[PDB]
Length: 47
Length: 311
Image (tube, rainbow over all chains, first blue to last red; front, side, top):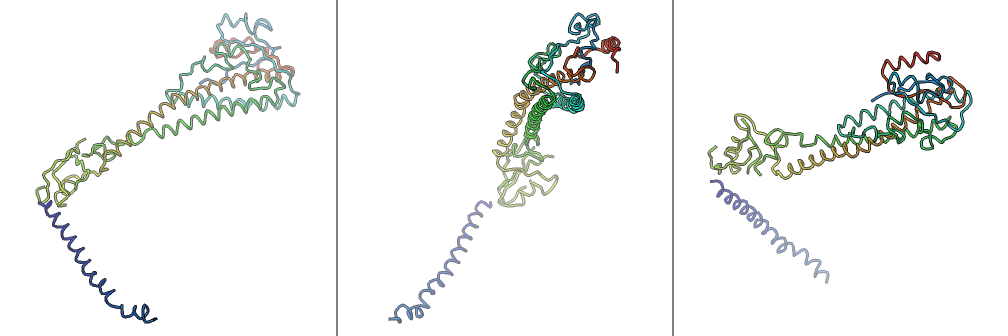
């Protein structure tokens, strides 16, 4: 009966991994969307 | 084997009917004594001090000969496959015991130098020591082979405390429990019989633990793959075969070295003939004694004959 439960456990592990990846995805996106007001002070403000 | 059994009598102290009768036509024929000898003097002999030094070193020479004899009789025979070298195969100085003891031809240039034997005796002793060292090397090789023998095959034949992978069934583990229903697919039966297998499954540890060690008698773990056990058994068989071959082929070389040691002992007896001649007669080597392995009655008769030079 736990043969099908193995699939459920694998699905739960994959869902947890995907949830962690998505949670870090917002931070990764904000790492570039934000703080570029500082990097533009060197990329173009130097000009 | 047999220790030294040579008689002591110079040329001037022959115990036979005549001085030259020691070799043949002696009264020993009537008593069936196997005594026989043949002269083989060296080129020259040392002085009185040299004779005394040789007599002193004769004790060490006899000790070395005894050590070689003990090694040859023990290492070869104990292997139960090296004692195949008979008297002819182990002939001393190229002649069997019938002829080796009847002559001193071993005094040729092989072990000694066919020269004043004061240092030639030491040289022959060193050669015999080298031969004994080779025999000891062969014995050590035989011991290492026996260490290779009694290998992993000495363990149990599977489904037991040791080497149980040979009887493995190859979520499950090698249990072989010698004298279950749950969510897990416990409806199974492994091939772990050399023993018995029980219903178990890795999906839920309840059935697996119950079958393995939970109740009754705990099972014995073993390697999962029987290929490793088969390889270990094959290696053990190969090591046993190699040990047997060494006891039959390398120990055949050991038996050849034992025959060489017998030749060295014949040379030592030839030297001891001249040593006794110097001790109880003049310096030049000349002896009329004999070397054999007679019975008690024959030795007593020889002593009665030679009582003119008793100790």
